[PDB]
Image (cartoon, rainbow, N blue to C red):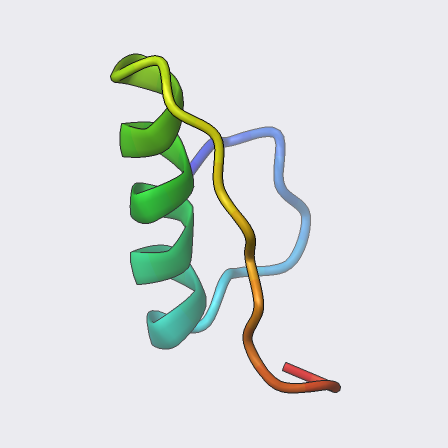
Length: 38
C-alpha cells in the first residue's frame, strides 16, 4: 500500500486498490460498486 496512508487498508480493500491501479495502468475507467460501509 502507498506509504502516504495513515491507517492500513484491509485485505478486501487492498485487492480493491489493485483493481483500481490496473484500471489506470491499462487506460480504462471503472465503477467501484462494493456495498455501503465497506
